[PDB]
Amino acid sequence: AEQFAVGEIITDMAAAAWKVGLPIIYLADMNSSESVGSDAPCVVKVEPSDNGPLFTELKFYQRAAKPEQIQKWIRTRKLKYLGVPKYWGSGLHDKNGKSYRFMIMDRFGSDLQKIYEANAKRFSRKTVLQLSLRILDILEYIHEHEYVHGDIKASNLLLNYKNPDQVYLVDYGLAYRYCPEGVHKAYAADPKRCHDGTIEFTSIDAHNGVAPSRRGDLEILGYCMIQWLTGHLPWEDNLKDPKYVRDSKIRYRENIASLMDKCFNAPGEIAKYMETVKLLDYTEKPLYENLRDILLQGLKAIGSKDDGKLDL
């Protein structure tokens, strides 16, 4: 089915005008006499208005992904960029007697998962450290704006369409506001939430059926880094049994040396990274700069620096 006639002009609720293009979710750009081409800088996502995930994602984008909000962060922290997609607007659209919600956001190039597979499911240490530094900036940002992602993975990491050295974290349909009005949620389940993440990468907290928090996000990144380096995780043979996966993660958490021995001479920064995350209490605020310093040591150990080169 078609929610839009291609080339039609839609107006968001702030009265900003956009033109809809072909599907890639549709390509989109500012309203003009020209057509929306394949180098369009925006997408328009459209779901039924009763779609829960789009609503949750829309609220995240409205609260934490305002263009000027992001740009202000970039300047004050003195970053080259920030891998949070920008929100450009949203509204309601009727068609065929049904109500649809739409949202305008940044368009991106390839996901990391496609590139990962193209490189025979291996990223270099350089790549993994550079990716991870930027994700730590993203996580720091969203955490400080009261949200956790809870599902970091290569297929949710998209490259800037016009810059392959900039990676962005997408999909906040099942993101969680862990800290509304500065009050941290308690160690317990959220009954209006049933997202456990992705089984292979999800946190022990999520495994235990409690709502995700900051430590959970960093833990997910830990598992990704190992996946990316080695092409494997210890529990990847039994992803159909969450009990097994949780058990394995709990045991490897208790003994990180044996995780390194299993997964790999292992990189010291990864082990140190995992060790720091382990110390975090559920409600505890991470020292993100310390975590970055730890990854920086990894770069210095291979004769490199934080040059912002993903080397993909």
Image (cartoon, helix red, strand yellow):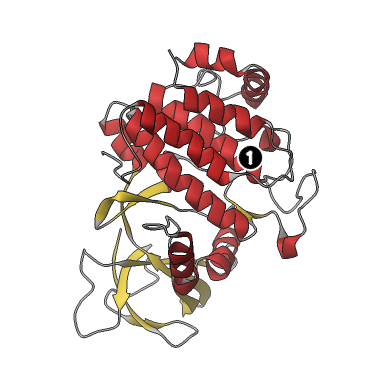
Q: Is residue 38 above or below residue 242?
A: below
The N terminus lies in which quarter of the figure? Answer: bottom left
Relative image position of residue 82 (x, y in whole percent): 42, 57
Q: Is residue 183 above or below residue 152?
A: below
Say whether residue 236 is visible: yes
Q: Is residue 159 above or below residue 256?
A: below
Q: Mark 1 falls on what kind of element?
A: helix
Q: Camera-side residue: 79 or 171? A: 79
Q: Is residue 93 above or below residue 1?
A: below
The residue carrying pointer 1 sits among few (fewer than 14), some (14 to 19) or many (20 or more) residues within 10 Å by Cα, namely: many
The C terminus lies in which quarter of the figure? Answer: top left
Relative image position of residue 12 (x, y in whole percent): 45, 82
Relative image position of residue 11 (x, y in whole percent): 41, 84
**Relative side of 105 to 92, left or right:** left
Q: Residue placed farthest to the bottom in the image?
A: 15
Q: Camera-side residue: 202 or 47? A: 202
Report the residue at 57% width, 28% height from top.
274
**Relative side of 179 to 40, left or right:** right
| Mark 1: amino acid | Gly
Q: Camera-side residue: 235 or 222? A: 222
**Relative side of 162 to 11, left or right:** left
Residue, disc 1: 216
Q: Camera-side residue: 268 or 125? A: 268
Relative image position of residue 278 (x, y in whole percent): 66, 30
Say whether residue 46 is visible: no
